[PDB]
Amino acid sequence: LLQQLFNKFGAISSSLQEILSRLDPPEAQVQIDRLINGRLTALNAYVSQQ
Amino acid sequence: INSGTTCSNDLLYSNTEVSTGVCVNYDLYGITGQGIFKEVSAAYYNNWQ
Amino acid sequence: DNETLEYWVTPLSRRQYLLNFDEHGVITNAVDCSSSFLSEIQCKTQSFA
């Protein structure tokens, strides 16, 4: 579950610090949304297994 | 990006001290973040690291 | 006086390895991840044993 915080899920980086120090607010959101969807999917699967 | 010695001098500041033991922001030569430093000894660094 | 000249050359390519780092930061061990089946197991477990 901790190794899911270092996948990109099709974004430019796995790090939220690296995205918010390179892109403007209209274009950082498109990258942040992909990380949010991947991490919510991983939490959903963990809760189903528990 | 965000590492090295080709630094833009638009936003100017002054060199502070590395305050160990407090939750500080840092911009160490382009490397940015929030953290807590601790002074230590370290033999693993060469002259290129 | 029975000496020899040696210059061994082999090509390079872009590929994934698993590297091992000790307490001095020295590369002790390496494995090419696509060379054999044991190396597939080693790179899949991220482990040298």
Image (cartoon, coloured by chain):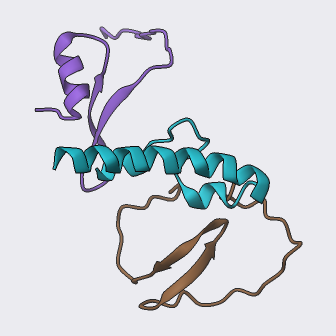
Chain colours: A cyan, B brown, C purple
Residue C46's x, y, as percent? 23, 34
Q: Nearer the viewer, residue A16 or B3?
A: A16
Q: Nearer the viewer, residue A28 or B44?
A: A28
Is C22 drawn above or below residue C8 in the view shown? below
As drawn, which residue projects farthest toward the right?
B10
Is A24 drawn above or below residue C16 in the view shown? below
Left or right placement of residue A46 versus residue B44 in this view: left
* The quadrant where residue A16 appears: bottom right
* The quadrant where residue C48 appears: top left
As drawn, which residue projects farthest toward the front?
A48
Number of numbered tags placed on the structure image: 0
* The quadrant where residue B7 appears: bottom right
Q: Residue at x 19, y 31 (%)?
A: C45
Is A44 drawn above or below residue C11 in the view shown? below
Instruction: Report whether residue B41 is seen.
Output: yes
Residue B44's x, y, as percent? 36, 61
Q: Residue at x 70, y 53 (%)?
A: A28
Left or right placement of residue A28 versus residue B24 in this view: right
Q: Residue at x 24, y 27 (%)?
A: C44
Q: Residue at x 33, y 47 (%)?
A: A44
Instruction: Report whether residue A14 is seen.
Output: no
Q: Nearer the viewer, residue B23 or A1?
A: A1
Residue C25's x, y, as percent? 33, 51
Left or right placement of residue C18 versus residue B15 in this view: left
Is C19 drawn above or below residue B10 in the view shown? above
Quadrant of the snapshot with the N terminus of chain C: top left
Quadrant of the snapshot with the C terminus of chain C: top left
